[PDB]
Amino acid sequence: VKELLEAGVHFGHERKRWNPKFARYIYAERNGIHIIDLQKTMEELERTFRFIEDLAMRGGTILFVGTKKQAQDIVRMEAERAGMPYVNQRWLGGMLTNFKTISQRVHRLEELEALFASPEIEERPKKEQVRLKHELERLQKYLSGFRLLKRLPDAIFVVDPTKEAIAVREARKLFIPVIALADTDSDPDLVDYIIPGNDDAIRSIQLILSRAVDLIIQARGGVVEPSPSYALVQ
RNA sequence: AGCCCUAGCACAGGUGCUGCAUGGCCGUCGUCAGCUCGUGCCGUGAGGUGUUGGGUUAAGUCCCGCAACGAGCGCAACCCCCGC
Ligand SMILES: [Mg+2]
Image (cartoon, rainbow, N blue to C red):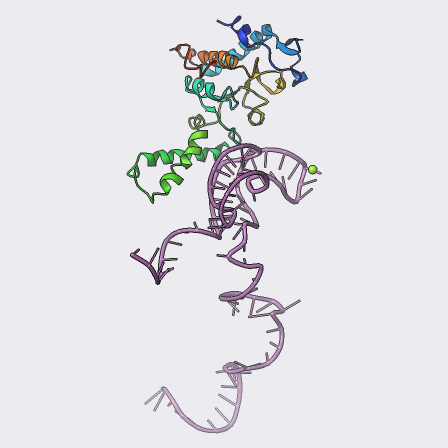
């Protein structure tokens, strides 16, 4: 049930913080704001959800990335409402390109899982029961959705692409397709598959990013409810 | 045969020169918080990033932040004495 839910509160965004490359996907500057053409969101959306459905039904791996204010949490939900990996707090230098190395973090994080459950559940020179047990905080806080990713992803899905362009950079560096929700902030030409929208409105980020996660499972049956995502939607 | 004695021979011996041919060992900047590597990233390149920044420490000690993520030689800790 799309169409009207788009123009709900999720159509147009920014003003004169713009990229002229995005000139095609705009209805008009009326009122001094940019209002983005909805008809062309839909057009782009099918082409995007097609890519999604196919990658999914061939049993792929989409890596989700949203590290901005209003994405932050809706991402770690819909990522796992889909059993898919995500990056949530901090995109690190070479998650995709130094992968093998950034991976010996995960390697060694769950070597500590193997000391939270151990004959060392209450022992070891007790100023390591923070030093280590607090090292597992950094490892926790960051590698939450990166831990499940075990070989480079098949796509990546970005929420604000100019916000997160150090990711996109590396995607392309490895020919990994890039799906992004983009708005006038941003440069389409290096989004591989484009959801031209509002990068900011939490209503928007939710409406879209969730409905993409219908597909991701409804290409495998057992579709769920309206799903845990209205963090404090107000 | 050994071992000894004189006549030879091959050799020994030299605190004789060269620390600007060396080894080892010491002193010095200085117990100063530094000096680097792996891979990634930036740069035509020498190189850079990392190791800069903000707070903090005796300290590159820790912390928050960040195209970096880690590691090695250091610092601290593992040894000795002194305190209960
Ligand atoms: Mg130059």
